[PDB]
Image: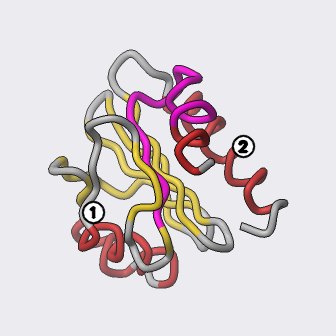
Protein backbone atom coordinates (compact mmCIF):
# COMPACT_ATOMS: atom_id res chain seq x y z
CA UNK A 1 0.00 0.00 0.00
CA UNK A 2 2.47 2.72 1.03
CA UNK A 3 5.00 0.75 -0.92
CA UNK A 4 2.77 0.74 -3.97
CA UNK A 5 2.19 4.50 -3.69
CA UNK A 6 5.95 4.96 -3.78
CA UNK A 7 6.65 2.33 -6.37
CA UNK A 8 3.69 2.93 -8.62
CA UNK A 9 2.17 6.36 -8.12
CA UNK A 10 5.51 8.13 -7.63
CA UNK A 11 8.50 6.30 -9.06
CA UNK A 12 6.55 4.14 -11.51
CA UNK A 13 5.32 7.22 -13.34
CA UNK A 14 8.67 8.48 -14.45
CA UNK A 15 8.27 11.94 -12.83
CA UNK A 16 10.56 11.32 -9.84
CA UNK A 17 13.63 9.09 -9.89
CA UNK A 18 13.43 8.29 -6.18
CA UNK A 19 10.77 8.65 -3.47
CA UNK A 20 9.74 8.04 0.14
CA UNK A 21 6.74 8.54 2.38
CA UNK A 22 7.36 9.64 5.91
CA UNK A 23 5.37 10.04 9.10
CA UNK A 24 5.12 13.52 10.76
CA UNK A 25 7.81 12.25 13.14
CA UNK A 26 10.16 11.78 10.21
CA UNK A 27 10.33 7.97 10.28
CA UNK A 28 9.95 6.26 6.91
CA UNK A 29 6.69 4.48 6.12
CA UNK A 30 7.90 3.12 2.74
CA UNK A 31 10.75 3.95 0.41
CA UNK A 32 11.89 3.33 -3.20
CA UNK A 33 14.55 0.66 -3.79
CA UNK A 34 17.92 1.76 -2.41
CA UNK A 35 16.75 5.23 -1.46
CA UNK A 36 16.90 6.06 2.17
CA UNK A 37 16.20 9.14 4.18
CA UNK A 38 17.36 9.38 7.81
CA UNK A 39 14.87 9.81 10.69
CA UNK A 40 16.97 12.86 11.60
CA UNK A 41 16.52 14.63 8.23
CA UNK A 42 12.89 13.52 8.04
CA UNK A 43 11.98 15.19 11.32
CA UNK A 44 13.71 18.40 10.29
CA UNK A 45 11.65 18.39 7.14
CA UNK A 46 8.59 17.66 9.16
CA UNK A 47 9.40 20.69 11.34
CA UNK A 48 9.91 22.93 8.27
CA UNK A 49 6.24 22.69 7.40
CA UNK A 50 5.52 24.19 10.83
CA UNK A 51 8.50 26.60 10.91
CA UNK A 52 10.44 27.24 7.69
CA UNK A 53 12.86 29.62 9.44
CA UNK A 54 15.51 26.94 9.95
CA UNK A 55 15.37 25.61 6.36
CA UNK A 56 15.18 29.01 4.77
CA UNK A 57 18.60 29.92 6.17
CA UNK A 58 20.43 26.62 5.57
CA UNK A 59 18.10 24.66 3.26
CA UNK A 60 17.71 20.91 4.15
CA UNK A 61 19.30 17.45 3.72
CA UNK A 62 17.82 14.26 2.26
CA UNK A 63 19.72 11.02 1.66
CA UNK A 64 23.18 12.61 1.66
CA UNK A 65 22.44 15.39 -0.86
CA UNK A 66 21.87 18.95 0.41
CA UNK A 67 19.14 21.20 -0.95
CA UNK A 68 18.19 24.85 -1.24
CA UNK A 69 14.70 25.95 -0.34
CA UNK A 70 12.76 27.26 -3.35
CA UNK A 71 9.28 26.87 -1.88
CA UNK A 72 8.12 26.62 1.73
CA UNK A 73 4.52 26.84 2.99
CA UNK A 74 2.28 24.87 5.29
CA UNK A 75 1.70 22.21 2.68
CA UNK A 76 4.75 22.16 0.40
CA UNK A 77 8.50 22.32 0.66
CA UNK A 78 10.62 22.12 -2.49
CA UNK A 79 14.37 22.08 -2.75
CA UNK A 80 16.64 22.38 -5.80
CA UNK A 81 20.26 21.47 -6.64
CA UNK A 82 21.21 22.33 -10.17
CA UNK A 83 19.10 20.37 -12.65
CA UNK A 84 18.00 18.09 -9.79
CA UNK A 85 15.69 18.68 -6.83
CA UNK A 86 13.12 17.27 -4.47
CA UNK A 87 9.37 17.86 -4.19
CA UNK A 88 7.94 17.26 -0.69
CA UNK A 89 4.31 17.62 0.27
CA UNK A 90 2.50 17.27 3.60
CA UNK A 91 -0.68 15.24 4.12
CA UNK A 92 -2.70 14.74 7.29
CA UNK A 93 -0.63 11.74 8.45
CA UNK A 94 2.55 11.75 6.36
CA UNK A 95 4.86 13.71 4.10
CA UNK A 96 5.57 12.66 0.55
CA UNK A 97 9.05 12.96 -0.87
CA UNK A 98 10.01 12.77 -4.52
CA UNK A 99 13.41 13.52 -6.08
CA UNK A 100 13.96 14.05 -9.77
CA UNK A 101 17.14 14.28 -11.77
CA UNK A 102 18.47 16.25 -14.68
CA UNK A 103 16.23 14.35 -17.15
CA UNK A 104 13.06 15.51 -15.36
CA UNK A 105 10.98 18.68 -15.60
CA UNK A 106 10.72 20.10 -12.07
CA UNK A 107 7.06 20.97 -12.50
CA UNK A 108 6.43 17.47 -13.89
CA UNK A 109 7.64 16.08 -10.61
CA UNK A 110 5.65 18.62 -8.55
CA UNK A 111 2.47 17.65 -10.36
CA UNK A 112 2.88 13.96 -9.62
CA UNK A 113 3.69 14.41 -5.94
CA UNK A 114 1.06 17.05 -5.21
CA UNK A 115 -1.46 14.87 -7.10
CA UNK A 116 -0.61 11.93 -4.79
CA UNK A 117 -0.96 14.14 -1.74
CA UNK A 118 -4.43 15.28 -2.74
CA UNK A 119 -5.42 11.66 -3.09
CA UNK A 120 -4.08 10.63 0.29
CA UNK A 121 -5.61 13.71 1.94
CA UNK A 122 -9.01 12.74 0.55
CA UNK A 123 -8.52 9.25 2.15
CA UNK A 124 -8.02 10.63 5.64
CA UNK A 125 -4.21 10.40 5.39
Left or right: residue 53 versus residue 125 is left
Please state which of residues 10 and 44 is positioned toward the viewer in this rendering: 10
At which x and y percent is residue 120?
Answer: 73, 56
Q: Vertical placement of 110 versus 78: above or below?
A: above
Q: Residue at x 40, y 31 (%)?
A: 100
Label 2 and label 1: CA atoms lie apart by 23 Å
Left or right: residue 46 versus residue 118 is left
Residue found at the far left of this picture: 64
Asked if residue 14 lies in the magenta stretch, the reply is yes
At which x and y percent is residue 50?
Answer: 51, 83
- Pointers 2 and 1 in contact (C-beta within 8 Å): no
Q: Residue at x 57, y 58 (%)?
A: 89
* Start-end of magenta stretch: 7-22
Q: Quadrant of the C terminus?
A: bottom right
Asked if residue 109 lies in the magenta stretch, the reply is no
Q: Residue at x 53, y 44 (%)?
A: 3
Q: Which residue is mark 1?
A: 60
Q: Which residue is mark 2?
A: 115
Which callout, 2 or 1, points at the residue further toward the start of the chain? 1
Say which of marks 2 and 1 sits in front.
2
Left or right: residue 93 versus residue 3 is right
At which x and y percent is residue 85?
Answer: 36, 40
Q: Vertical placement of 20 versus 7: above or below?
A: below
Crowd band around label 2 with a 10 angstrom C-alpha radius: few (<14), some (14–19), many (20+) = some
Q: How many numbered discs, if any?
A: 2
Crowd band around label 1 with a 10 angstrom C-alpha radius: few (<14), some (14–19), many (20+) = many
Secondary structure under tag 2 reads: helix
Secondary structure under tag 1 reads: strand
Amino acid sequence: SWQTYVDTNLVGTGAVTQAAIIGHDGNTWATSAGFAVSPANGAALANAFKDATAIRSNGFELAGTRYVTIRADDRSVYGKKGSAGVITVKTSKAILIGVYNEKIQPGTAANVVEKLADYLIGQGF
